[PDB]
């Protein structure tokens, strides 16, 4: 669900596309969509626009506000990219022609064997799940149902990697892939780690709060005393029960932790393990349909209903717990590397450590294949 429009400045005398002879657009990277719009205009309006190629949607927008072109094509996915450098962009423009487009996100792929990968995307926002934002949580869960082993692989939000699809395979912080869409995040991580991602789950703050509540809160073992959300919550060393608001604080805090984002990553992992413990309780398994009903409008997933039913019932019958291991991709913070989405800003990114990448990839393979972790 996205659209392409022809946009002009808010105060333009231009009312309709027939008044135009050309439009500025990034045909180098979004040509398929652009040509569809152009063919649509030629057929409904009998107007045949020439294209002034721009290097990107952002560059087109810049040309428009600089009075270097009268009109641009805007793909709605990229409004959220323009917004990164121009937060007021919406008030600067009007749209004079709009065409809706469609695309299904990731088809799920059923693993032929005992092992599958689920990508968990956590989005930086409250409200309706359809809201577009960056993906600040990016965790791969590798599950082997034969060995009963799960590996959580965390990739830091600032990891500097080639971003698939809308990212044009150019390097940027991983969290930006989320703005292009969940399929961009999925393909980005598939390419990084060389594995197929069978399924995804996408959720935001509002989704997470609901889930922890429905589960009765979660229990974790905390290793370091800390407080979260500007002091609102305090977590002592030891066994801690987390209600929903506490859990959200627990997975968001970074700066005061001994190891910063890495410790936050570990805290997120602790919460996942805790959620899994609740979801595999006999009560939760028996009442899985109620949980599906209670979360379906706030959590997106491509896990098929039949697959959920198989996973649940297998666990119901055989019982037995999964052993969970965790790992995180390591790197070095830098301020001097360019962001593809935000070419005018100096951003903090994490340059990936190649030795860590090799170890992380091998661990994913070991768990999938039923081999002991190194
Ligand atoms: C909807 C789902 C997936 C499940 C619900 C339905 C049920 C009952 C499922 C049961 C499945 C089951 C019982 C068994 C499945 C087979 C099995 C025994 C194991 C396999 C597990 C599997 C295949 C799927 C289960 C997936 C599970 C249980 C959990 C995935 C982890 C989840 C759902 C959430 C964790 C997300 C998290 C830790 C954080 C999200 C927080 C958010 C939204 C944002 C954080 C952003 C941030 C940290 C900072 C940004 O803020 P700032 O920095 O600006 O302050």
Image (cartoon, rainbow, N blue to C red):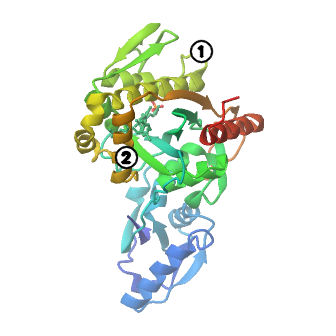
Quick check: 354 left or right of 239?
right
Image spot of residue 288 (x, y percent): 27, 39
On screen, residue 178 above or below 153: below
The dot on residue 46 is none
Is residue 157 visible to the viewer in this orientation of the structure? yes
Question: In the image shown, does 143 or 120 lie closer to the viewer?
Answer: 143
Residue occupying the point 66% across, 55% down: 170
Count the labels in the image.
2
Residue occupying the point 42% across, 10% down: 239
Q: Quadrant of the C terminus?
A: top right
Q: Nearer the viewer, mark 1 or mark 2?
A: 2
Image spot of residue 52 (x, y percent): 59, 77
On screen, residue 75 above or below 234: below
Q: Quadrant of residue 151?
A: top right
Question: In the image shown, does 1 or 357 lie closer to the viewer?
Answer: 357
Q: Quadrant of ligand 1?
A: top left
Image spot of residue 75 (x, y percent): 46, 66
Q: Helix or strand or loop: what does disc 2 sit on?
A: helix
Which numbered disc, 1 or 2, marks the residue that appears first in the sequence? Answer: 1
Image spot of residue 147 (x, y percent): 55, 34
Q: Quadrant of the N terminus?
A: bottom left
Residue occupying the point 39% across, 12% down: 240
* Mark 2 burial class by Cα count in 10 Å: few <14, some 14-19, many 20+: few
Q: For the view shown, which residue lies furthest in the right direction?
A: 355
Quick check: 330 left or right of 57?
right
* Mark 1 burial class by Cα count in 10 Å: few <14, some 14-19, many 20+: few
Quick check: 184 left or right of 99?
right
Is residue 19 visible to the viewer in this orientation of the structure? no
Check disc 1 and report the residue beneath it: 258
Check disc 2 and report the residue beneath it: 310
Q: Helix or strand or loop: what does disc 1 sit on?
A: loop
On screen, residue 230 above or below 329: above
């Amino acid at each position: 669900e996205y659209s392409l429009s022809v946009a002009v400045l808010a105060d333009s005398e231009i009312e309709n596309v027939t008044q135009l002879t050309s439009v500025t657009a990034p045909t180098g990277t979004d040509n398929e969509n652009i040509q569809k719009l152009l063919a649509d205009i030629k057929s409904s309006q009998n107007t045949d626009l020439t294209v002034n190629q721009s290097s990107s949607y952002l560059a087109a927008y810049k040309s428009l506000i600089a009075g270097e072109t009268k009109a641009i094509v805007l793909n709605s996915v990229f409004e959220n990219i323009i917004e990164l450098e121009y937060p007021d962009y919406a008030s600067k423009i009007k749209k004079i022609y709009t065409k809706g487009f469609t695309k299904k996100v990731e088809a799920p792929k059923t693993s032929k064997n005992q092992s599958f990968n689920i990508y968990v995307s956590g989005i930086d926002t409250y409200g309706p799940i359809s809201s577009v934002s960056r993906s600040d949580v990016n965790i791969l869960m590798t599950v082997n149902r034969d060995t009963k082993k799960i590996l959580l692989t965390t990739t830091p939000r600032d990891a500097y990697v080639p971003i698939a699809d809308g990212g044009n395979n150019q390097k940027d912080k991983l969290t930006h892939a989320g703005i292009y869409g969940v399929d961009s995040s999925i393909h980005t991580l598939e390419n990084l780690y060389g594995v197929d991602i069978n399924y995804y789950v996408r959720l935001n703050f509002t989704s997470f709060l609901k889930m922890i509540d429905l589960l009765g809160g979660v229990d974790v073992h905390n290793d370091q005393e800390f407080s979260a959300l500007h002091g609102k919550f305090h977590f002592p060393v030891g066994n801690v029960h987390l209600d929903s608001e506490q859990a959200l604080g627990f997975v968001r805090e970074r700066y005061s932790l001994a190891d910063g984002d890495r410790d936050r990553g570990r805290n997120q992992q602790k919460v996942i393990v805790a959620i899994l413990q609740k979801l595999t309780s006999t009560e939760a398994l028996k009442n899985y349909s109620t949980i599906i009903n209670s979360l379906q409008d706030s959590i997106q997933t491509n896990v098929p209903l039949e697959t959920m039913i198989n996973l649940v019932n297998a666990q119901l019958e055989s019982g037995g717990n999964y052993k969970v291991n965790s790992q995180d991709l390591k790197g070095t913070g830098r301020m001097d590397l360019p962001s593809y989405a935000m070419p005018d800003s100096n951003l903090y990114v994490m340059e990936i450590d190649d030795s860590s990448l090799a170890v992380v990839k091998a661990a994913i393979q070991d768990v999938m294949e039923g081999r002991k972790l190194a």
